[PDB]
Image: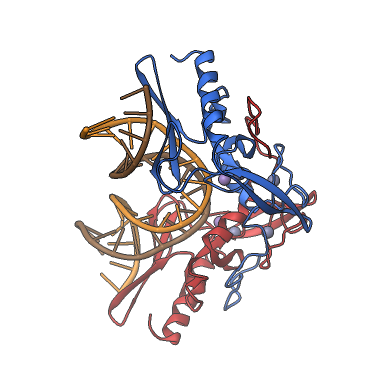
Chain colours: A blue, B red, C brown, D orange
Amino acid sequence: ALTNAQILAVIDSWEETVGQFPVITHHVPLGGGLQGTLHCYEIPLAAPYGVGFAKNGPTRWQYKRTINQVVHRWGSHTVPFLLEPDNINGKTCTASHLCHNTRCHNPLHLCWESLDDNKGRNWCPGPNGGCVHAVVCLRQGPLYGPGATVAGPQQRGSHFVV
Amino acid sequence: ALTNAQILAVIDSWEETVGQFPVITHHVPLGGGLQGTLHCYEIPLAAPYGVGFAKNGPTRWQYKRTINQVVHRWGSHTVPFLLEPDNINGKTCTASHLCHNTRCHNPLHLCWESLDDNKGRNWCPGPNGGCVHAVVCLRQGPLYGPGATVAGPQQRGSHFVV
DNA sequence: TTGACTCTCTTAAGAGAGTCA
DNA sequence: TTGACTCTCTTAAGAGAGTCA
Ligand SMILES: [Mn+2]
Ligand SMILES: [Mn+2]
Ligand SMILES: [Zn+2]
Ligand SMILES: [Zn+2]
Ligand SMILES: [Zn+2]
Ligand SMILES: [Zn+2]
């Protein structure tokens, strides 16, 4: 099995490579009518992506290193968390974008949490709009707002009460 | 079926049958430390479910009627909305449970909206905790809260900024 | 050992359609 | 005509593994 020192070396080579990705400045809603700035380190749109990186889906990538003649591979956003527990409350831990930008691999924009926690950040009002996430959001979720509901609760007769 | 009269007849037959489902009282968090009461009309756990109803999945049902000698079938929660547009902004409209109770078929607990709007209600703070849904939530979402994040954003070196 | 492709899978909110009696 | 089963599919946040040179 890979030693802790070997895992730290994978994390270090991953950081070295991702740190050379293009850095894109984005202005983002924080909630409460305030605006902030995030700096995303974005994997390229097409090959080559960077040393060790390859695309396995439209917005999916993997990181690969060969150690002592054995090929090891990880989801490209999971590498910062290789020294962390991989489940919690019986749920698998997932890499969760606080910047809501899939191509971004900035580890300061990622956290490690259940898929439900991950998804729920899409609707959070944001760090200045009432976020209650213990690991605080970096921005208001892209789907926060009144929604676009087509039809509300209704009945034709009188068979029901709320 | 095709005619407005035929569609109204489907909605009315559905309301009459669902109106005879057992009414189960559920006390729910509203947000803001307050609690409310919802009355769900719950489809039975096993056959028979009611005239026109059949189970196609662990928590999926369909409603079926024979019109003009032809069988017409719908998802069991979609029937209240048969006269509404079936898409919005190019996204499919879905039946969305405000009571977060799949077995419930109370149309006063249903709305008609995109799958994203639907999902997002799971994390809403609720009608007394800051819900901004234009079609208002009936309760705080079951997944609202601080979360259980295992690891937050972090780096080993000095290559990244927020 | 490495790059650039290929495939299918998970989850939890939702769907459509066929086989028998 | 009605009932009671069977199967796979959609979406958008996420995954693992194979082939070839
Ligand atoms: Mn996410
Ligand atoms: Mn729902
Ligand atoms: Zn980012
Ligand atoms: Zn938040
Ligand atoms: Zn209900
Ligand atoms: Zn709401």
Query: What residue is rendered at 74% in x and 59% in y?
Result: B127
Query: What residue is rendered at 62% in x and 57% in y?
Result: A143
Count of labels shown? 0
Q: Can you tell which quarter of the image residue B75 is in?
A: bottom left
- Residue nearest the observer in this picture, B57 or A160: B57
Q: Is residue A15 left or right of residue B26?
A: left
Measured as percent of width and height from the top left, residue A115 is found at 54, 41
Measured as percent of width and height from the top left, residue A11 is found at 54, 25
Q: Is residue A40 above or below residue C3?
A: below
Measured as percent of width and height from the top left, residue A80 is found at 56, 29
Query: What residue is rendered at 78% in x and 59% in y?
Result: A33
- Residue nearest the observer in this picture, A39 or C7: A39
Measured as percent of width and height from the top left, residue B103 is found at 51, 55
Quadrant (top left, top right, bottom left, bottom right) of the N terminus of chain A = top left
Quadrant (top left, top right, bottom left, bottom right) of the C terminus of chain A = bottom right
- Residue nearest the observer in this picture, B104 or D12: D12
Figure quarter occupied by ligand 2: bottom right
Q: Is residue B110 left or right of residue A31?
A: left
Q: Is residue A160 visible?
A: yes
Q: Can you tell which quarter of the image residue D17 is in?
A: top left
Q: Is residue B41 visible?
A: no
Q: Is residue A99 left or right of residue A56?
A: right
